[PDB]
Image (tube, rainbow, N blue to C red; front, side):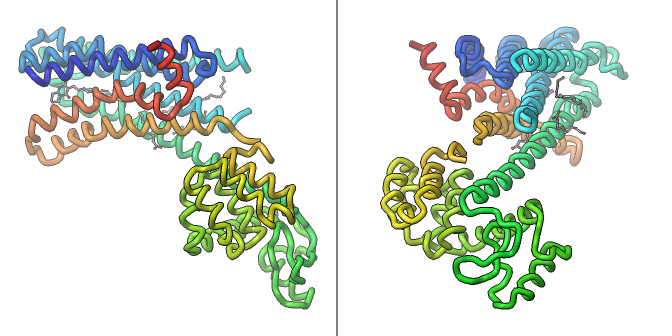
Length: 423
Ligand SMILES: Cc1nc2n(c(=O)c1CCN1CCC(c3noc4cc(F)ccc34)CC1)CCCC2
Ligand SMILES: CCCCCCCC/C=C\CCCCCCCC(=O)O
């Protein structure tokens, strides 16, 4: 047949791509991390799908019927559920290892942590699929387990929806931490450049300000400038505030600065194109020069928009801004060029955390239409086009071959590693 050939071709792609993932991590220094060890554990889960499950699936297409015995069927379904649950439980362990790398501060303590995580993945996958060999410990005596009306509920909830929610809660907790970091990094970036003042003072235009460039009022009365300060800090500040109280005010000024940047037709385009780190450098400039002045760097802003980080740095050093405050300018131009916090303190893990979430998302993209279909079989009893049911099942098995394709795109170390193995 034609569809059986494609399935066998898929088996080759699954094996070819995932054998690469194993050898690459096994032989490349910069690829020998905790996450990458859980990645090869993920590659083994997919390697076993190609070898212990797909032969049953390609057989299932040539024959056109489930012409196994009842024990062969139970074995196949048990292995199919297990090797796919290991993929889900591996993506869960990957997120958790991604949480500890971001949220927590050893070459020996970490390796022991990976060994425990991997063992839990495969022992749990076994214990979850082991009931399927024995009638799901339910009432289905003389029939295969996939004929059990409770199999769909079991493998959906236990093997998929519960790993789905837990992993989703971890990544949400991960995003929240990274967003607190960006709000903290920008505060430090400007208390180094602009300066943190805890008592009321006058800016260069005569207005009473406090914190990091926060005009209390444009009124000349000092007593009135204190009224607006206490109405915003909540307490009788008496002129002095905490560095924490000033950090709350700074975040308000930053958010306000973004509402205007996006409402500025000359700054909104480049602002979208910018990485989050380079986006803080643009906020630094509007904090110093205002949105009016930054919009005058048209030749430079287009180069940031065109990813020309080299030239955008060379042009910005030819401005009257670089000549007026050169120390701060060189620090911000460095941030526009490198895209990190080297000038001020940059986490090198974010790139790996973004790839881990992309793999988890592609996973959900591939299997969710399959489990959405199950919900429809139960809801309306409408018999679904078997070509569609067969498609969403194959799409889920296809997921076993997409992960190595993602490592070549989003990871320079994985991409250059594979090309060295093929040469
Ligand atoms: C062979 C077959 N053939 C057909 N259909 C089938 O459902 C099947 C079986 C499909 N297996 C897909 C993976 C499932 C699974 N279990 O646990 C998991 C955990 C995960 F994270 C992700 C997936 C799973 C268990 C069922 C439907 C009718 C068309 C022909
Ligand atoms: C021993 C070194 C580890 C240091 C970081 C801690 C690692 C994770 C610690 C505890 C994991 C919590 C147990 C997870 C329970 C989830 C069960 C569930 O929600 O269904």
